[PDB]
Amino acid sequence: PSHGSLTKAGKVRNQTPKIPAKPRKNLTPRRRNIRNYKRRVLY
Amino acid sequence: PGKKSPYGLFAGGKLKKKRQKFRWNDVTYKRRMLGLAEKYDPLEGAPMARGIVLEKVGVEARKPNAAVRKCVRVQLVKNGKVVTAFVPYDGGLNYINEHDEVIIERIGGPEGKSLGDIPGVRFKVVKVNGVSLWAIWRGKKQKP
Amino acid sequence: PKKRKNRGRKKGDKGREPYVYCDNCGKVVPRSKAIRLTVPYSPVPPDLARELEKQGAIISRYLVTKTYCINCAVFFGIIKVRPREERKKRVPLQQ
Amino acid sequence: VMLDLLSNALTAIKNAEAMGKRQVVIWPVNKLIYYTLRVLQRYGYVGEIEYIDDGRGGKYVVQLLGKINDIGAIRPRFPVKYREIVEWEQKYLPARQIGILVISTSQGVMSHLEAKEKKIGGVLLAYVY
RNA sequence: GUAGUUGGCGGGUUAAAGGCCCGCCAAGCCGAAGACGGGUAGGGGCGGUGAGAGCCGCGAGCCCCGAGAUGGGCACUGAGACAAGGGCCCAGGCCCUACGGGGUGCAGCAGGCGCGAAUACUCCGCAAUGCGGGCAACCGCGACGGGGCUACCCCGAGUGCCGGGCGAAGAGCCCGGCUUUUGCCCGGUCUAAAAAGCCGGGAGAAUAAGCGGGGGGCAAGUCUGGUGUCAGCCGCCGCGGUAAUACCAGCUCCGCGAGUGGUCGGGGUGUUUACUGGGCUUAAAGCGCCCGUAGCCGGCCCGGCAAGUCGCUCCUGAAAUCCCCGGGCUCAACCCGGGGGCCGGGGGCGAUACUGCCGGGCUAGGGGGCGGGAGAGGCCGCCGGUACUCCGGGGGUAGGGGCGAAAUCCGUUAAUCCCCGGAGGACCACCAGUGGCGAAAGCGGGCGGCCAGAACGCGCCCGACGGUGAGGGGCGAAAGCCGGGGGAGCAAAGGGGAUUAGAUACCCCUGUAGUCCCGGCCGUAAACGAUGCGGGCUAGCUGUCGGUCGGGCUUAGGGCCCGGCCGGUGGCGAAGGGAAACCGUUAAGCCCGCCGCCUGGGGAGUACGGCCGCAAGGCUGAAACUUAAAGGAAUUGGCGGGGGGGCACCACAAGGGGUGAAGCUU
RNA sequence: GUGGGGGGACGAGCAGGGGGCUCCCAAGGGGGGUGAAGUCGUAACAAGGUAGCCGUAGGGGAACCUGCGGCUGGAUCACC
Ligand SMILES: [Mg+2]
Ligand SMILES: [Mg+2]
Ligand SMILES: [Mg+2]
Ligand SMILES: [Mg+2]
Ligand SMILES: [Mg+2]
Ligand SMILES: [Mg+2]
Ligand SMILES: [Mg+2]
Ligand SMILES: [Mg+2]
Ligand SMILES: [Mg+2]
Ligand SMILES: [Mg+2]
Ligand SMILES: [Mg+2]
Ligand SMILES: [Mg+2]
Ligand SMILES: [Mg+2]
Ligand SMILES: [Mg+2]
Ligand SMILES: [Mg+2]
Ligand SMILES: [Mg+2]
Ligand SMILES: [Mg+2]
Ligand SMILES: [Mg+2]
Ligand SMILES: [Mg+2]
Ligand SMILES: [Mg+2]
Ligand SMILES: [Mg+2]
Ligand SMILES: [Mg+2]
Ligand SMILES: [Mg+2]
Ligand SMILES: [Mg+2]
Ligand SMILES: [Mg+2]
Ligand SMILES: [Mg+2]
Ligand SMILES: [Mg+2]
Ligand SMILES: [Mg+2]
Ligand SMILES: [Mg+2]
Ligand SMILES: [Mg+2]
Ligand SMILES: [Mg+2]
Ligand SMILES: [Mg+2]
Ligand SMILES: [Mg+2]
Ligand SMILES: [Mg+2]
Ligand SMILES: [Mg+2]
Ligand SMILES: [Mg+2]
Ligand SMILES: [Mg+2]
Ligand SMILES: [Mg+2]
Ligand SMILES: [Zn+2]
């Protein structure tokens, strides 16, 4: 059948290179719709 | 083939008996009324249960797909029944060991039965030793 | 789908048919659904120039009716497989 | 076996009207048939209602005007209270302005409009539109 | 099913009626309108969901009623208990002890262990609301009130505002100005006292955003890196096997936001439970057919009642909850005031249209009749027709039979073939039909006898006597079973000859049950129109059967033709219906009744139980589990050891030359 | 006030059966059903190469074969 096994558990997760990501904080509910109003309804 | 049947003004009692007779043709109604969910389900009517991992066993995906979905065999504490529980996530089986308490929970899918390409498995692991497996996999916590 | 409104045998308002036996066969059918072609028949075909009006030779000609099943009737060309529109057209079976 | 004459009569009108017939004969008949047809004729759904005298109960010959879109008898003859007739009104009729119900109240058979003005309910008979 | 069980009579006991208990007498009491038995559950106010009907119980928390205090019993006192922090006994625990004893059971408020997926402080006050006691003052109260903890439900907000530059119009960074909700500190007020709230003051942008997703459903990336049908995703569909928009990552974007997700349960979804409002020819679904009990549904007219029903009013349906209106907390959530409802019960007064009951009268549905005809309708008796097989005799030799071809086989103790006779069992050719009869199964020669059921004609009789029909009953092909008789032909099983790779099949020869009759059993079928029964309405044209009426002819016939009516039996086809095939006055159309049945596939007409049977077996009939389709009709094609037509020296026919063999080149 | 013997109603508990209702454990088998395609044939779909199917009976490695009756859902809506 398939050439998988329990010995390959998570093989791809340890194969991707580790690229650090920037820190990020998300907006409050009021600031989100201010952003969406400015970017969709406006130009 | 004509005039549905007990349509009289004073046919209320007979009409109610006839409609109750054919409710049993509905599998959903018969299961709920007969207490079949809480007699054959290993979780025993609960949404989740505890268990002890015994052996890491691998089930194969159905014919069109090709893979070895990595599950584990669990024995429920409250019943002693042995069930196969799917361990999700990439590398999630590596956070599992032998003889560790895991919280067993339904895998979803139609009607509480198995999921898409995984044949004959109804449960998935959510907690390992009292900590959520998604938390360990995301790094937000570490296994105890 | 119900091919043919007749059911394949013009039985009528009854429950059971007496049924017959098929010549060259025995697969057969009831009295309806059985082909019953009739042919003129006569021994010694066109010898009537040298017979009959030669010596006395009183010759005989016996109308014979033959009974067959769907297998034998299709086998001997008595029955073809007509198109759907042609199934409802009543043609005699060449006697 | 013939059971309800009013449903039989009302379905005859529906059958004959759908063929674009000028008239329809009705038999057998009772007073309930007559008093219903009077309410129908009062609302312009039916022409003249002539009566014939046989040994077998009698007949009515009703002239149709093409004024019927649908018709039928409500079964069973449901009791209805005056405050309830609005609910039964929207069950069998299209639009708030179109069509009537035939009710059999203690003051006699009337349209559902004439029952609402009298502030009484009764036993439902039929619907017309 | 019940045997103090159901009732009667006389007593006892009780605060009080009662088989509550007792003495006697009787056989009654309950049940298919579902007893009895089993299972589940405290009941209600009510709550969730849906536009609603409705479905569900999250019918836990708040209020009312009930029951209980480790299991089971029994008593004291008292107005009241057979008493949760009183008593006694048994069972089952545990605790202290000086061994002689004595306590105790948190389903009280905190609290611990245990179980489980799952859970709060061993805090403060009797100030509010009440209660017990007191003349009162006042006292007590883990009731109650207060706060603590807890992602409990709902409500109002913050996590900045203005302008500018860089950035992209975003995020973010920086600059300039503003505010302090909020966080922190302080004062008054509040609070039983605190806390929080409120009022006021100080510094200060300063103290504060996540959760889930971007292939479709479904808003969001054919951007990039990694892996390469592995790992992983995936409610469904579906991806991943080198260029992945679906996996792991980065960037970016989307939804909602102090929340956002996962698994469960309910509702919607869902006209997949259908009262509103489904379907049953073929998709699942009409019992094989019929007689009928309960039930449900039932013609017309007249008079009476007023039960149902309708209108008004009253007593009610606790409060809370719900809807509307007004008001008070900053608005809000919430609290207060008022009206409605809370689908019902009963009272009084009115109406009598429909239903109900009572009475009188009808004939339209039904039944009973009379007349002439029709019919393979049934049971019984008698007879026949050919054909067949066999037996006896005569003619005549040597083959017959069978097959694709043979062979087995029959035949030289005379066959097949022909003639004269006998016996036997089954069948009823043509006529003869979408002909007839019957409820279905089914019924085909003639004569006769006894029956049955219909159709038509009728100014005959009764007067609604009707329809359907759960449960109950009866009939019910073939095969098969029991016992007897019979046995020509055929023929399961078996024997042999062939064929074949095999051939325990297809063919041939042979062959026994069986097929036939009688008595009984079985009770099934593609028992089919795959179409339940009864009634009414809705263009027509055409074939045919029975009766009848009118006209025209007469094989002067019970005969024939034309037309009308009624009743059957086919075809085409209005309106209409249907997914379509198609149905269409013999509906699958428009309606009125009643019964049966269906609710994705497989598991499975399987298992258990029960009943039935001599047996075979039959009827009734699941679930776990597994699964995303199974399925209907129709279209295009492909294909066929199906049919028809056309064509071609890369087909054949008529020819010519060859190749295939030798040596050699390739 | 009592102490014995006894009779009564109520009635635990301990001994026993008796029945069910349920529920587990059980050497061994019994009919099944799913995989992924291993073996043997080729039963169904076309006249599937012996038209197919239903009930029943017998038989056979197995699909299945044969006898009887039925159906067309047939490969025939058509005799003279
Ligand atoms: Mg699936
Ligand atoms: Mg039949
Ligand atoms: Mg007394
Ligand atoms: Mg008693
Ligand atoms: Mg509480
Ligand atoms: Mg007790
Ligand atoms: Mg006590
Ligand atoms: Mg306790
Ligand atoms: Mg106080
Ligand atoms: Mg809020
Ligand atoms: Mg810029
Ligand atoms: Mg304070
Ligand atoms: Mg994210
Ligand atoms: Mg991504
Ligand atoms: Mg989109
Ligand atoms: Mg996705
Ligand atoms: Mg349906
Ligand atoms: Mg039938
Ligand atoms: Mg049945
Ligand atoms: Mg009946
Ligand atoms: Mg009344
Ligand atoms: Mg109020
Ligand atoms: Mg109330
Ligand atoms: Mg019955
Ligand atoms: Mg038989
Ligand atoms: Mg033979
Ligand atoms: Mg024999
Ligand atoms: Mg049927
Ligand atoms: Mg249909
Ligand atoms: Mg038609
Ligand atoms: Mg069954
Ligand atoms: Mg059984
Ligand atoms: Mg084609
Ligand atoms: Mg040639
Ligand atoms: Mg050569
Ligand atoms: Mg084959
Ligand atoms: Mg055999
Ligand atoms: Mg044989
Ligand atoms: Zn034949």
Image (spheres, coloured by chain):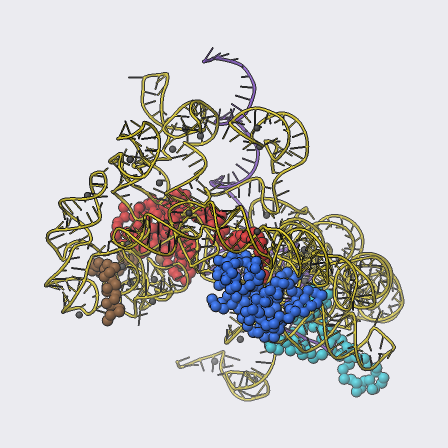
Chain colours: A brown, B red, C cyan, D blue, E yellow, F purple
Q: In the figure, residue C69 lies in which quadrant?
A: bottom right
* Residue appearing at x 67%, y 69% in the figure: D52
Is residue A18 in sight in this rendering?
Answer: no
Residue E129 shown left or right of residue E640 in the figure:
left
Residue F25 shown left or right of residue E223 in the figure:
right
Position above or below: E437 against E131: below
Q: In this view of the protein, which residue sits in the foreground, E474 or E240?
A: E474
Q: In this view of the protein, which residue sits in the foreground, E119 or E483?
A: E119
* Residue appearing at x 76%, y 75% in the figure: C64
Image location (x, y in percent) of residue F57: 66, 54
Is residue D90 in sight in this rendering?
Answer: yes
Image location (x, y in percent) of residue B136: 28, 51
Q: In the figure, residue F44 lies in which quadrant?
A: bottom right
Image location (x, y in percent) of residue E530: 61, 63
Ligand 25, what quadrant?
Answer: bottom right
Residue E501 shown left or right of residue E119 in the figure:
right
Q: In this view of the protein, which residue sits in the foreground, C18 or E100?
A: E100
Position above or below: E46 against F53: above
* Residue appearing at x 62%, y 65% in the figure: D34
Number of numbered markers: 0
**Which quadrant is home to the C terminus of chain A?**
bottom left
**Which quadrant is home to the N terminus of chain A?**
bottom left
* Residue appearing at x 41%, y 62% in the figure: B64
Q: In the figure, residue E242 lies in which quadrant?
A: bottom left
Image location (x, y in percent) of residue F62: 57, 57
Residue F53 shown left or right of residue E176 in the figure:
right
